Length: 407
Ligand SMILES: [Cl-]
Image (tube, rainbow, N blue to C red; front, side):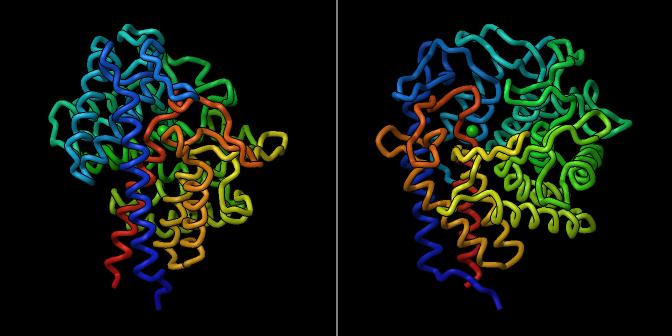
C-alpha cells in the first residue's frame, strides 16, 4: 500500500542530483579552490569566482571540505575525491590541529599560522565529523585517533553534567569563554541549538566508526536533550538559544535547522540502534518536517530563511536550507510513506536547479532574493563550504537508490 513515484521519476531525479554533485559542486571545489601556494584550500572565493589564497582560513570550512570529499570518495569511488580529501586532511592536521593543547583552532592565516586560537565546540564537532568520515573512507588510524582525542577534550572541558549539554566555546587552553557566539548574527546566550545539533551530528558519525559505550551514552543524552529542551511540540520548531538550564532565550525560527534536525536526529538514534527512543524521535522529526512544509516554504517550494526575534520573515533563500530540505523531505517521505514529502523534495530540487545553482559561475549562490535576484555574496567563505549541498546530493542519491530497490 505504498505510494511511490514511478521508476522513471525516481531515476530521473537521482540522475539530476548525481550530475549536480559531480559536474557542478565537486567540480567547482576540486578546480577552483585548491591552493598551490600554501597547500590546502583557499579561504574565500569572491562573487566573481576569483579565489583568494591569502585570505584567512576557517577550521569549519576546511573540516567541511574534508568531510565532503571523504564522503564522496566513499560513496562514489572517484580517485580525485580521495586526492582532494587527502589534501584537506594534510593541511588540517598540520595547521588546524593544536598539537600542544588538542582540538582545532578557529582560524589560521593562509600560511597556517594560528590567528584565532579559540576552541569552539562547533568547530571541534566539525573536526570530529570530518575526521570520522575520513576514517570511514580509508580506515585511517590517525584520523580516528584524532577524532577520539577531540571528543575526549569536549567531554573533559565543556560538558555540563548538571544541566546537560555543553559549554560552547573555550580559549586555546580550554578555559571557557563568555562569548560563545559563532558570529554577530547569533544571540549572546550560553547555549545554542546550532552548536548542540552539530555535536550530535559529530558524535553520531564517530559512534558509527567507534561504538564506545560511553559515547553511546553521551549521544543518547544529546538526543534526549533535543526531545526535552530544544524541540518545541507546541510549534514544531526548534528553540534556538537558551540559558545554562535550557530556559528558552529566543523566539526566532530557523526553517533550515528544523528540517536538518528532522533527519539528523533520526540518523543519530539509528546509529545507536536505540529502538526504544526511536518512536519519540520519529514523531518529533516528522513534526519538524510538517511544520517546515506548512510554514517555512515559499509558493515555489523553496525555504525561507528565518522568522527573527521580532517576528520578521526573512524571505531570502539561502543555499543550505534548500539542501537540508532536499534531504529532510526525502527522509520524511521514507519515514512516513506520505508522498507529499516527495513532492516537496522534488519542488525544492526544481528550485535548486532553476534558481539556487549558479550555472554561469559554478556551484550554488549563497542567497537568492524573494524576487529571484541572486545576491553578490562570496561563493566560498568561512561559512560556505561544500558540505550542506554536497551531503544533500549524496544523501538524496543513496535514498533514491533505496527507493528504487522497493520494486
Ligand atoms: Cl557548507
